Amino acid sequence: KERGASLQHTAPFGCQIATNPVRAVNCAVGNMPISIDIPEAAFTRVVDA
Amino acid sequence: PSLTDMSCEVPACTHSSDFGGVAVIKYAASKKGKCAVHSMTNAVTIREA
């Protein structure tokens, strides 16, 4: 009766909270480094362009 | 054949030791025919004769 607001309503950074399993979704915090290995076949030469 | 109004540009150059450079030469030919090509320096070698 006295539970109060749940984390999906009170969490910072707009976090969505779900259970089964317990997880936080789409928290707008910080940044994410990405490294991509791009094959030579994916490139077009300047003389082809 | 005689050529005039000639100019050269280099879309790309890499000193890869395997013909990593490419050059494009614009020309105005007096008539259709074949022309020999030769480098005027020892620092640069041209693949096509």
Image (tube, coloured by chain):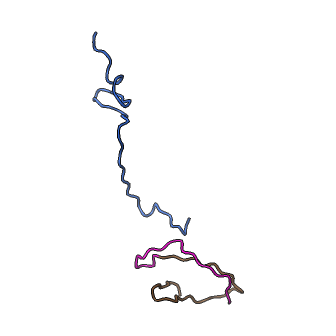
Chain colours: A blue, B brown
**Quadrant location of residue A47?**
bottom right
In the rendered view, tell whether residue B27 sits above or below residue B40: above
Magenta region: B1-20
Residue B20, image x and y in percent? 45, 76
Residue drawn at x 51%, y 67% is: A45
For residue B37, side relative to residue A24 (left or right): right
Front-most of B34 and B20?
Answer: B20
Residue most extreme to the top: A1
In the rendered view, tell whether residue A46 sits above or below residue B35: above
Residue B9 in magenta stretch: yes
Residue drawn at x 64%, y 82% is: B6
Residue drawn at x 50%, y 84% is: B46
Residue A41, image x and y in percent? 45, 63
For residue A37, side relative to residue B38 (left or right): left
Residue A27, image x and y in percent? 36, 34
Front-most of A38 and A16?
Answer: A16
Front-most of A26 and B47?
Answer: A26
In the rendered view, tell whether residue A20 sits above or below residue A34: above
In the rendered view, tell whether residue B18 sits above or below residue A17: below
Which quarter of the figure is the N terminus of chain B placed in? bottom right
